[PDB]
Amino acid sequence: EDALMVTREDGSFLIDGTLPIEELREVLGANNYHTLAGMCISYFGRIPHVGEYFDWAGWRIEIVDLDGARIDKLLLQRLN
Amino acid sequence: EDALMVTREDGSFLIDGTLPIEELREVLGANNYHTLAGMCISYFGRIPHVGEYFDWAGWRIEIVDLDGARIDKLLLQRLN
Ligand SMILES: [Ca+2]
Ligand SMILES: [Ca+2]
Ligand SMILES: [Ca+2]
Image 1 (tube, rainbow over the protein chains, first blue to last red):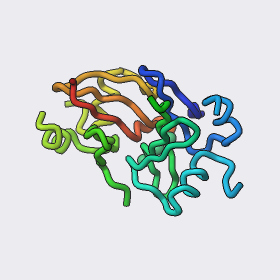
Image 2 (tube, helix red, strand yellow):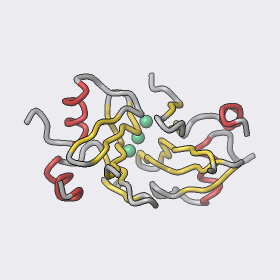
Image 3 (cartoon, chains in turn green, blue):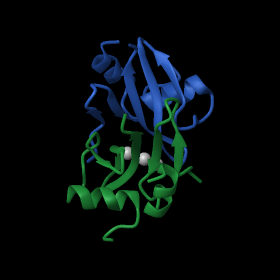
């Protein structure tokens, strides 16, 4: 089944909302949530629009796909 | 229901694979397919991996989310 994380040409990451935060911490070298999508909902306090973003642990996390209410895909880019 | 197209902060577009090609042509100012996902499958001749891309009509089209076999979200960026 679908890869949970993939690397783009520029080194940024496209990541499934279900990735556990523990695993996210490990792969970036960087509660009321235990997954990436959960962390997003916690931060925005609502279901974010695609294209909204926030910064966390020296990374920018941008919503890139929703499936209905599900935060399905995020883009992670290291802050410059 | 879900927006078919959204604009990112840098002006690039995140677009649903179901967007018809006619409508895509209009929004970019730019068969065996009539949708964006269809055009992708036609180009690759297989279901592409997330992060694969091609150039078409002065734009780069990058796969950014799959749902199983469905090409669910694409990133469109104007070639520099
Ligand atoms: Ca979607
Ligand atoms: Ca997906
Ligand atoms: Ca999806």
